[PDB]
Amino acid sequence: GVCRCVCRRGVCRCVCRR
């Protein structure tokens, strides 16, 4: 349920976990 977004080079990679 927790989504973290890692933004790099304008691209955000979101990873959802629980």
Image (cartoon, helix red, strand yellow):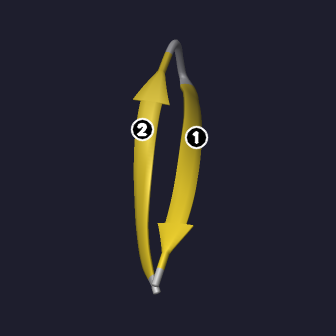
CB atoms at circles 2 and 1 under 8 Å apart?
yes
Name which residue lies at 54% across and 56% down: 15
Please name whichever residue, 6 or 18, is drawn nearer the observer in this view of the structure.
18
Name which residue lies at 48% across and 73% down: 17
- In the image, residue 14 sits, relative to residue 18, either above or below, namely above
Q: CA distance from mark 2 to mark 1?
A: 5 Å
Q: Amino acid at mark 2?
A: Val
Name of the residue lying farthest toward the top = 9
List the residue tagged with mark 1: 13
Q: Which mark is residue 6?
A: 2
- In the image, residue 14 sits, relative to residue 8, either above or below, namely below
- In the image, residue 14 sits, relative to residue 13, either above or below, namely below
**Disc 2, SS:** strand
- In the image, residue 3 sits, relative to residue 13, either above or below, namely below
Point out residue 2 in the picture as x, y percentages from the top left corner: 39, 77
**Disc 1, SS:** strand
Q: Residues within 10 Å of mark 1 (few under 14, many from 20)?
A: few
Point out residue 4 in the picture as x, y percentages from the top left corner: 39, 58
Name of the residue lying farthest toward the front = 18
Q: Amino acid at mark 1?
A: Arg
Q: Is residue 10 left or right of residue 6?
A: right
